[PDB]
Image: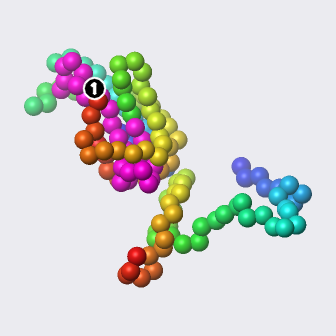
Amino acid sequence: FKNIDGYFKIYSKHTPIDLPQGFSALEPLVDLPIGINITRFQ
Amino acid sequence: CVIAWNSNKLDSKVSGNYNYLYRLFRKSNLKPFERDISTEIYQAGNKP
Amino acid sequence: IEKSNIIRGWIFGTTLDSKTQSLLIVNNATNVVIKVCEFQFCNDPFLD
């Protein structure tokens, strides 16, 4: 999850299986023009 | 692009219009492409 | 790291109250609902 210049971007990935040792990439899936102030999440 | 034009005959009333409001006080400067709609009074002193 | 889809969604905002803006992302088994509104929370957020 990233939020820059008033835009909210969400990248995601799924896979089958402490975190495992391996290499994988993530693809862009959401961009929204929210444009608010975000400091804490749940 | 930025476009500006005149709307005198569409937003002027003899008795005066007060539907349009602006903000004058804030604690910190505004981030680009940001919208705030708060109403809390500007804390200039200690007592709320 | 999950099985049976226990984790559902997320909340984003400044103070998470009825006063200022809030984003909800919910995944109630049918569609990915994203909703940015002026939203109220409780102290024990959970779904059936």
Mark 1 surroundings within 10 Å by alpha-carbon count, few (fewer than 14), some (14 through 19), many (20 or more): few
Q: Chain of mark 1?
A: C
Q: Find residue C29 and report its image quarter.
A: top left
Give the percent coordinates (x, y) of residue B32: 53, 56
Q: Position of residue C35 (x, y in %)?
A: 46, 36
Residue nearest the observer in this picture, C10 or A8: C10
Q: Give the answer, above or below, for where C33 lies relative to A6.
A: above
- Locate residue C35 relative to residue C3 in the image: left or right: right
Residue A29 makes an appearance in the image:
yes
Amino acid tagged 1: Asp
B15 or C10, nearer to the observer? B15
Q: Quadrant of the C terminus of chain C?
A: top left
Q: Position of residue A39 (x, y in %)?
A: 35, 53
Q: Quadrant of the N terminus of chain C?
A: top left
- Residue C12's quadrant in the figure? top left
Residue C14 counted in the magenta span: yes
Q: Main secondary structure of the magenta part?
A: loop
Residue drawn at x 43%, y 38% is A9
The magenta region covers C1-24
Question: Residue, x 36% and y 54% (percent of image)?
Answer: C15
* Placement of C9 over or under B11, stated as above or below: above
Residue C10 x, y percent position in the rendering: 33, 37
Q: Which residue is mark 1?
A: C48
In-front residue for pair C16/A16: C16
Corner quadrant of residue B5: bottom right
Q: Residue at x 13, y 27 (%)?
A: A20
SS class of the residue under badge 1?
Answer: loop
Is residue B7 rendered magenta in the image?
Answer: no
Residue A4 visible in this rendered orientation of the protein: no
At x 51%, y 63%, the residue is B39
